[PDB]
Image (cartoon, coloured by chain):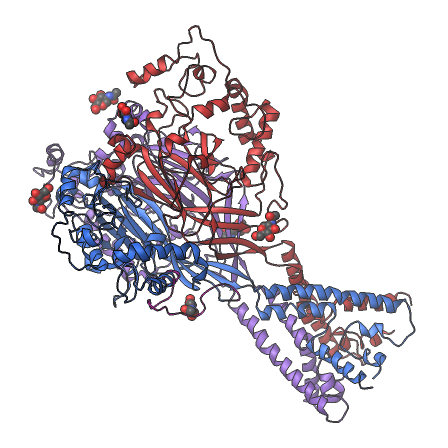
Chain colours: A red, B blue, C purple
Amino acid sequence: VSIQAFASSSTLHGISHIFSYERLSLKRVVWALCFMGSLALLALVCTNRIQYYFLYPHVTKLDEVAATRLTFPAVTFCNLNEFRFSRVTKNDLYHAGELLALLNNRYEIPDTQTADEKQLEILQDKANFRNFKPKPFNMLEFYDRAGHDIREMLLSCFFRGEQCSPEDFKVVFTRYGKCYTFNAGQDGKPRLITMKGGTGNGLEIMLDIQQDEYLPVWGETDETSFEAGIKVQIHSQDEPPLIDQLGFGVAPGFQTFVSCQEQRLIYLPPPWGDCKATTGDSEFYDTYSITACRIDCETRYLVENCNCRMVHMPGDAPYCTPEQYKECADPALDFLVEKDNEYCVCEMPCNVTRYGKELSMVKIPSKASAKYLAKKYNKSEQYIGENILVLDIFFEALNYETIEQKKAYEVAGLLGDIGGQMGLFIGASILTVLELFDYAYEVIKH
Amino acid sequence: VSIQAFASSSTLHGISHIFSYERLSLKRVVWALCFMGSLALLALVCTNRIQYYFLYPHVTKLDEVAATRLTFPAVTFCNLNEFRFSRVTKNDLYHAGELLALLNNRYEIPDTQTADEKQLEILQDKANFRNFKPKPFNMLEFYDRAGHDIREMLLSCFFRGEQCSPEDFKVVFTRYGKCYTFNAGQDGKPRLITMKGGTGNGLEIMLDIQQDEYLPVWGETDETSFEAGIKVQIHSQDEPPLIDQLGFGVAPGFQTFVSCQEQRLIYLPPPWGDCKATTGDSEFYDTYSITACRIDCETRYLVENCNCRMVHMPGDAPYCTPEQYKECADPALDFLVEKDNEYCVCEMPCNVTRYGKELSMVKIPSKASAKYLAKKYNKSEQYIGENILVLDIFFEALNYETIEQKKAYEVAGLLGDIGGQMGLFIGASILTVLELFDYAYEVIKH
Amino acid sequence: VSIQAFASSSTLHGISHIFSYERLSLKRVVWALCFMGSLALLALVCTNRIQYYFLYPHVTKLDEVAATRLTFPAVTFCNLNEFRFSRVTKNDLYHAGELLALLNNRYEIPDTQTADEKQLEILQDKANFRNFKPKPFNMLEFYDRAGHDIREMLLSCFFRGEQCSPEDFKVVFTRYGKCYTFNAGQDGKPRLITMKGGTGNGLEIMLDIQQDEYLPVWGETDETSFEAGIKVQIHSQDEPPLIDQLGFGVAPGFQTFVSCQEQRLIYLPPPWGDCKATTGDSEFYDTYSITACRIDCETRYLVENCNCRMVHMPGDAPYCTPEQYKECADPALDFLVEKDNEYCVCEMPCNVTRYGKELSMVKIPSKASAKYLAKKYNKSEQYIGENILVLDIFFEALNYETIEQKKAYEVAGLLGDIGGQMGLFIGASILTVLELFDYAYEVIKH
Ligand SMILES: *[C@@H]1O[C@H](CO)[C@@H](O)[C@H](O)[C@H]1NC(C)=O
Ligand SMILES: *[C@@H]1O[C@H](CO)[C@@H](O)[C@H](O)[C@H]1NC(C)=O
Ligand SMILES: *[C@@H]1O[C@H](CO)[C@@H](O)[C@H](O)[C@H]1NC(C)=O
Ligand SMILES: *[C@@H]1O[C@H](CO)[C@@H](O)[C@H](O)[C@H]1NC(C)=O
Ligand SMILES: *[C@@H]1O[C@H](CO)[C@@H](O)[C@H](O)[C@H]1NC(C)=O
Ligand SMILES: *[C@@H]1O[C@H](CO)[C@@H](O)[C@H](O)[C@H]1NC(C)=O
C-alpha cells in the first residue's frame, strides 16, 4: 500500500529505517548514505565476478599418477639418407635422376672433383642414355626398393628382455623416405606394454647405418646430407609420424639411452580453452591428432592444386612423377606455407598423450668388445666405430604425469559469489528483487 | 500458530506472499511457481558444489623462489663394468666364475674365437682346477676388491673451485657393483653447499674409466657389456642410489656439463592427493623416499623367500652365494616383478626434493692439451681419447622451483558457496531451517 | 525501545525466538545454544578465509597458445678459448702476459715439458724482453684483435633456408672474450621471425673452431682449457648474454639439433608474488631482466671499489689494466660473491620470455661427404673430424607455452565467502551490524 507501509514489512535491510514512521531527522540520512553506498559497493564488486566468469578462466592441476602396466610409445625412426646408393638403377636415374641431386640440368653429371675412380665408374654406366629404352616409373616403388632395408640395418632388437623381430617393424613414408615404426599398434597388432623401468625393460635396438651406402657428394647442392646417423620421433600410436618436424637424432658409435616420461595432457573445450571438442574423424586417418590434421591439410591441397599426392601422403591418389615435382608440387608447398598459412589451422584435441625425453650418451664399443663385434657381423674394426649405434628407449618409473585444466569458476561458484555479497551488502535475494517488482506493479496502477 | 500467521512473520522470502491473508488470486500461484522453482534451482546447484567438494580437488601453485646458499645434490656414479679384470683370481673364478659370464656350464671356457694370446693366457692359469684348494668366499668381499678403485679412476675432482678428495667419495653397492657417492651427507659429514652458478661453481671430476680393465667378451652371452663410459644418477642425500633405474650416462672423451635445477615438490595427503602422510621410518633406512621403500620392498622379500640378501641390499643378513643366486635369488626376482607386482606398492611422500638435468657435451681434449695430458698421467695418446672424461654438475642460478599443490576447495569455501546461493535463492540460513522445524514441531502436537 | 520489542522486528534470525514475549521455557535455551554456537561456527570459519586472503595466494594457469609467426631467439655463442695463439704479440706478452697463464711470476716461461720445437720457438721470440720498447695497451683492444674472428670461423650460416651473413653476427664481450650474437635485434635491426618448425626452418651454422689456434698447455695452471668446442646460451633479445652461467655447449664433429620451445612466463607483483613491478630502467641497459640487473650489480661495484670496469662490462668507464686485475679486480669479485652476496639481490621481472632446449646429436661427416668437405675449404681429412661442427636451433611447432599466475582469491571472492557464510549462519549483513549498532546507540542514552 503505502511506501512507509511497504518498507516496514519487506526483506531488504535498509528500508526499514529510511522510510520509518517518524519525522525527518539525522538518522534518515545516515541510513540513506549507508544504504546508497552499500548498494554501490555491491554494484562494482558483483560486476567484477560477472566479468571474471565471462572470461571463462581455468587453472591447471598437475598430478603424478602411479601405475603398473604402461604402454610403450611408437619408436619411429629412419636413416638420414633418403635411399641407398647401390640400389639405384639406370632407369631410376632417368625418370628421377635430376631430383636426387646427382645430375645437372641437361641430365648430365656436375663437376666430378673429389670423386673416387671406383665411385664414379659405378655411376658412369648409369648415365649412358645411349639407345635407352626406359621402364615405367613410380616414386612409391622407388622408395620401396632403393631405401634402407630393415633386414640389413637392424642387427639386434629387444623389448623387455625378450627378442624382437624385423617383421614387427612397420614401414611408413616421410620426407626422408623409407621409415619404420616399432610398436605401431595398427593392422590389428595390440600395443605392447612394459612392467618395469630401467635401461633393460624398454626397447634396445642395435642398428647399422650403412655409411658405405650413402649418396657421395661431389657438387655443392642445395640439400646435400653431410651428417651420418638416424632421426627418431617418439609419439603415441594414434599420431602419424612427423620425423621431419618433431624428431630428435642419435649418433653412430654412441649408445644413447633416451629416458621417456609418459604425459597425459587434458585441455578444455571452448569457451574455456581451445581444443577439438568432438572426435573429428579425418578423411585419411581414423583418429584425430595435431599431426593427422596437418597432413590432411596438405593432402587435400595438393590434390586440388596438382591432381596427385606426394610419397609421404595418405589416401588413394596416384603419386606425382618428378615432372609434376619440379613444376607443380614444389612451387605449391611454399605457396601454402609462406603465403596461405593463415587459411589452414589445426586445433589440437584435448585428450592428448605425449612423451618427454631425457637424452644420455654412452660410447660403444669398448676395446674388450671391439674385436668381438668385428667378426660376429663380418665387419672391419674401422667400420664398427662409425656405423654401429644402439638406441634405448624406456621409462624411468611406472608412473605418468597428467596435466589437466580445471575450470576455475563455474556457474555454481558465480551464484555463491553473487549472493555471497548480495546477502552481505543489502541482504536481498532473487525473490526480494521480485518482491520490489511486486510492490512497484501495484503503485503504477494507483 | 496458524499457517497464515507463521508465514507472515518468518525469515523466508517467499512465504510472506504465498500464504497471505487474502483470497486465492493469480498472484498466489505466481509466487508459488517462482518459489518452487527457486527452491529447485537452489537444489541442483548446491548439490554441484557438495559433490565438487566430495571429489576433494586440488590445483597446483608453481613458484620460483630465489635463494643464496643451495645444497649440492649427491652425485652418484659408477663405471658400467661390474668389476675389474686384473683383480679376479683363481678362487674368484671357482665360487663365482659361471655367474660372471666367462665360463660354460661345466666350469670351462666357452668358444675362444676373437681372443688375444696375451688376453687368454692370463685367464688360462685362472681356470686350471688341478689340485685346487678353494678359499672361503663372500660376494661382498668380491665387490670390495675386484671393483673399480676410486684412487685409480679419479684424476682430479673439484668443488666450488676448491680441491676435492677420494676420501670424500663414499662407497655404495648397486647392480653395477662398486659405486661411489660424492656429497653423501651421511656418517656425520655435513652436506656441502654452493654460493654461485656457472660451470666452475659445481662439481668437476676428471675420471679414468680403465678400458683395458674391462671384461673381454669372447662368447655371445645374455649380459655382455659392449659400451664404455659411466652412469650417473643425481638425487638428494636422503634417497638411496638407484643408478640401475634413475641413472643417465656420460661418454669418454666428452666433457659433459650437466646443468641441474633444484625442485622442491610438495604433494597433498589423502583424501586430497596421494602421499605418505606420516614420516614412515623404514626398517633399513632412517628416512623414507620412493626408492628406500622399493629396496625395503625387495629386502624383506628375499629374506622371507631365500634366507639371505643380495650385495645391493641393506640390513644385516648374510650375503647369498652364487649357489643361492642361480637357484633361489634370480628366480625370485621375476616371480615378484612380473607375477606379484601388485602385492607391493610404494606411496611417494609429499615432501620430495628432485633435481632436473639439462645435458651438454664438449669434446675433450684439444690438440693444444693433447700431449700434456699424455705425459702428466703417464698415458698414451690413444689412451687419452677413449678413457679420459670429465663430468660437471652445477646449478644454473641460485633459485629453486617449487611445485606445491593447494587444496582448491576447503570447507570454508563450501560454506561460502552453500549460503552464497542459499541466501540468493530463498534467503534462508541454518536457523531458518531450524525455524521451520520449530513451527512444524508445534503443528504435530495440535 | 524494549529488548523484546527490538528483537521481534530486526533482521537477525535467532533473536526473534530467544527474546520472545513469553515466560522462560526450554525453547529459549535451545534457541540460545543454537545461536551462540552458530555465531561461533561463523567466527572460526570466517577467520579462515580472512587469513587465507591475507596470505595473498595464487595458482598457475598453463596454456599452449598456437601462433604463426614466432620470433627467433638470440643464438649467442663463443669458442671456449679466450683468444687465438697466432694473434698474440711481444707487446701483448708484456702488459698481459702473466694473466694469460703462459708465464711465470718473473715474466719468464714455466717448465717446457711436452712442448714442440715449432710450438716453443714461435713463443720464444715473443719473450725476449731485450731492449724492449713497449706499446700502449688496452684489454678491450686485445680482445678485439686476438680473439676468434667471425669471418674465419663460420663456414656457412643459414636461416629459414635463406642465406646468412657474418655482418649479421654482432660482437659482445663475456668472460670467454670475443663472443658473437646472431639475431641480436639491437642497432635498429628488426628481430627476425620464423614461419615453420623442423630442422630446416631455423638457424643452421657450420663453424670451424680452429683447434690449431688454441693455447698450448705446458704447465699445470689454475685455468687451463683442455676441452675443444663452443658454448651457447639461448635467450631473448632483451637479456644481455650470460654464456658463462646460462650456457650449454656442443661438440666438434657432431651436428647438434637444439630444439627450442618458446615460453612466455608471467609472474605476479607483490604482495601476491615476487616480481619487479615497474619497468626499472637500469643505468647501463635500456631494458630490465634478471641478467641485466646482475651485471649492473657488478659494474657499479667495481667502479666504486677499483675505479674501472672489466672487459665484459657495460658503461663508459676505462678498462682495467692487468696491474689492476691482479691487485684490485680479482680480489674484489670474491669479496662480493662470497662475503657480501646478501647486499645485492635482483628481483626477476614478471614479463619474462624464456626458451627451453632439447638436445640431440648427429655425427658429421659421413664418408660420402668426407672427401668433399676436405677440398672445399682446403682442409685435411684429420682436420675435418675435430674442427668442423654444425649447430641447428629451431622450434618444434609454431606454438608457445605460457606459464601465468592467476590470483586465486581476490577481494570479490572474499566478500562472496564472508557473507556466503554470514548469511548461512546468522543471516546478517553489513546493515544488520549497523542495525545492532543503531539499537545499542539508543539504549546507552536511556
Ligand atoms: C577424454 O578422456 C577422459 C578420461 O581421461 C574421458 O572421460 C573423456 O570421455 C575423453 N574424451 C574424449 C573426447 O575422448
Ligand atoms: C665377409 O666379408 C668379406 C668382404 O670383406 C667377404 O669376402 C667374405 O666372404 C664375407 N664372409 C662372410 C661369411 O660373409
Ligand atoms: C614438509 O615441509 C614443510 C615446509 O616446506 C613443513 O612445514 C612440513 O612440516 C613438512 N612435512 C613433513 C611431513 O616433513
Ligand atoms: C709409465 O708407464 C710405462 C709403461 O707404459 C712404464 O714402463 C713406466 O715405468 C711408467 N712410468 C711412471 C713414472 O710411472
Ligand atoms: C606484461 O605483458 C602483458 C601482456 O602479456 C601486458 O598487458 C602488460 O602490460 C605487461 N606488463 C609490463 C610491465 O610490461
Ligand atoms: C691450401 O693449404 C695449403 C697448406 O696446407 C697451402 O699450401 C695452399 O696454398 C692452400 N690453397 C689454397 C687455395 O688456399
Left-right relation of B334 to A56: left
Percent of width and height locating residue C255 = 35, 35
| Residue furthest out toward the top | A131
The C terminus of chain C sits in image quarter:
bottom right
**Number of numbered tags placed on the structure image:** 0
Front-most of residues C79 and B3: B3
Chief secondary structure of the magenta portion: loop
Q: Quadrant of ligand 6?
A: top left
Left-right relation of A176 to B151: right
Front-most of residues C268 and A390: A390
Left-right relation of C369 to B48: left
Percent of width and height locating residue A127 = 39, 12
Answer above or below: position of A217 versus C44. above
Percent of width and height locating residue C221 = 17, 47
Q: Quadrant of residue C432?
A: bottom right
Residue C216 is at least partly visible in this image: yes
| Magenta residues, start to end | B270-293
The N terminus of chain C sits in image quarter:
bottom right
Left-right relation of A171 to C339: right
**B274 is within the stretch colored magenta:** yes
Residue C111 is at least partly visible in this image: no
**C316 is within the stretch colored magenta:** no
Percent of width and height locating residue B278 = 43, 70
